Image (cartoon, rainbow over all chains, first blue to last red; front, side):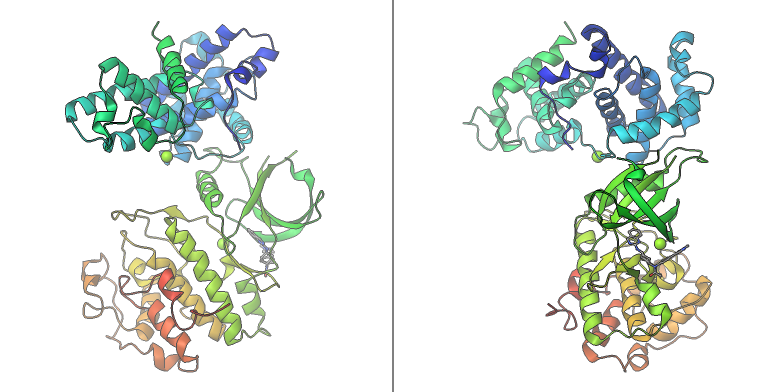
Length: 238
Length: 293
Ligand SMILES: CC(=O)N(c1ccc(-c2cnn(C)c2)cc1)[C@H]1CC[C@H](Nc2ncc3ccccc3n2)CC1
Ligand SMILES: [Mg+2]
Ligand SMILES: [Mg+2]
């Protein structure tokens, strides 16, 4: 299957056919992703499992609407399945306890009389919706592979990676994983890190005399795509 | 897609989370097998073991390995959809009334070992090879099946895996003696057992307990001891689990009715020391398999 959209077609969700305005949808996406991130972090789950769950969450809502599927329940379901896929399984009872610890009485209301049942039921649908394409890769692994191949000041390179890492965490609140492959997100956060620290990254490559340092890691990425990804991530801090 | 899209004909297996079923695709007419995966009456949702099996299957694209066409659902379980295969290997042998020629076996093993080499090159251990998990249709074509115990293994370094794997009769001695940091050689031992059982029809080591299984293997392949397998003393149950006597290898005198090229292969595949056992790649250069169309 193809899990990537133009920005034009992203604004045309099930939640938009059903009357929900874009600001609210974008808020429900951030709240949901952060919810997954917070629950998983509290359970000790690590960065790939959290990211897998958040991807499932973003994809799921390109086929269903928030008016029908309350977001915190869907989040808990995506994480539960991610744990199984990434071989870091957690019991559904523990995901609920942790969810409950982070939500308030109103928010947790979404889970209903039987919080566990509501999640198990949703797992059947989630799996159908993501077409059992369970394997997913994330930007972190490429951030590390690409950065490892730079040779030069280790402190500067480490600072770059560390900033770029945080920028990956931030990208997850957005629909960037539905627009671009993780390989590209990685290059972009490096590029962003590059700008803000004012590091010329080409100088740490084998070829200091080529501007487009990223071409050794991915082929064919226009600078305006990176700029675009940079602009979207920066919008979170405005 | 839904399971009403298929015509169910009957039951053709028990899988680990449901029956397997034979069926007709209503759009195309083709015959298929449907592995059911039951959910209702589950405590931790869609079975984690099924999730594991499915990730692995989706990566496997080889002529001699089972290939999953799609997954479908009820009008509540899911069904994994595969292209249908006429027999499993255990079924042909058990009737009797079936002899395999030297050339039937040649063909059959080239396919199996190319199947297994593909899996191993892509870092998967099958960990449940045996006659009932090898499928075979009337075109003479083989498919290796049931990846319900498979898993990714690490070749850049060594790691500890689950010890109780492979059914007793196809289980190699390193696992009998308790090893956890094992290798793809465990799958080759099981395939070595197939090769023997192809020439006899009876499975070659048929005990019901581990201790007795070790006895049966020793009695043919030699008792494991450090002269033939130096690392063996470093295994957890080497002191605990001994054959009665210290037996001499006598595989070749037992199987001297087999053709000689096959005997060399068989000897190599059932070598006790996993690091001396041949790899799937190596088998395919043996004289028995080297030139097979
Ligand atoms: C004796 C025998 O040869 N068989 C048999 C084995 C059990 C049974 C049986 C009936 N009841 N029970 C409990 C077992 C009835 C026939 C055949 C074995 C291969 C089967 N086909 C097949 N093809 C592709 C598949 C892909 C994935 C998973 C399963 C697949 N199976 C066809 C039946
Ligand atoms: Mg991964
Ligand atoms: Mg089986």
